[PDB]
Amino acid sequence: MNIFEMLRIDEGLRLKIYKDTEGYYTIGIGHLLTKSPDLNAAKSELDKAIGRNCNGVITKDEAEKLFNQDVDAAVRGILRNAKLKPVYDSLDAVRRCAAINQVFQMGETGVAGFTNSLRMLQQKRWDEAAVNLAKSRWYNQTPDRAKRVITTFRTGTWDAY
Ligand SMILES: CCB1C=CC=CN1
Ligand SMILES: [Cl-]
């Protein structure tokens, strides 16, 4: 296991525009296109992202290219966030994957509400952190995926995958 295999499990692969768990137009491996309800706006974002007129459909190679870009942007964003970087750098490699997964799903400006979880993780109080992480809209809206990510934070193993 690694971050690519982990997110591939959690996000799936679809080659035509679809709506994600929040109702937002998405393609590929969890590549969010727009929060706009206008499919034409999503199609324009897709064409801009791929560099050609896609008419709402991409290839597997194109999906994997967007995925590589999105994972890299997620990690770099963590490193450029003064609240997230110290916690991320304190973690082992498996738990770092759980952190990337969470930012990939919720956006770096969507983890803002996780101050107390972040402190418990940096303290390595793993069971307490796991309890705190589940007291969240994140967990309640996507409980089976959140349970996998939290088990990864709790144990530092890939047992949930
Ligand atoms: C909330 C995402 B996250 C970022 C760094 C460390 C742990 N989790
Ligand atoms: Cl709650």
Image: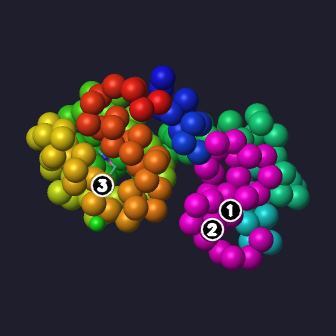
Three-letter amino acid code at the position of disc 1: Lys
Using the numbered discs, state the Cα–Cα distance from disc 1 to disc 3 in whole angstroms: 25 Å
Q: Secondary structure at mark 1?
A: strand
Residue on which the image places disc 2: 23
* Residue at 73% in and 58% down: 18
The verdict on label 2 being within 8 Å of ligand 2 is: no
Asked if marks 2 and 3 touch (Cβ < 8 Å), the reply is no
* Nearest to viewer (mark 2 / mark 3): 3
* Residue at 18% in and 38% down: 126
* Residue 121 position in % (x across, y down): 19, 43
Q: Of the residues under marks 2 and 3, which one precedes in the sequence? A: 2
Three-letter amino acid code at the position of disc 2: Gly
Asked whether 7 or 160 is in front, the reply is 160
The image quarter in which residue 46 lies: bottom right
Q: Give residue 134's mark.
A: 3
Residue 104 seen anywhere in this rendered image of the structure: yes
Three-letter amino acid code at the position of disc 3: Ala
Q: Secondary structure at mark 3?
A: helix
Q: Is residue 55 above or below residue 14?
A: below
Q: What span is colored magenta in the figure? A: 12-39
Using the numbered discs, state the Cα–Cα distance from disc 1 to disc 2 in whole angstroms: 5 Å
Q: Give residue 19's mark.
A: 1
* Residue 147 position in % (x across, y down): 39, 45
* Residue at 59% in and 45% down: 11
Q: Residues within 10 Å of mark 1 (few under 14, many from 20)?
A: some
* Residue 75 position in % (x across, y down): 42, 41
Asked if marks 1 and 2 touch (Cβ < 8 Å), the reply is yes
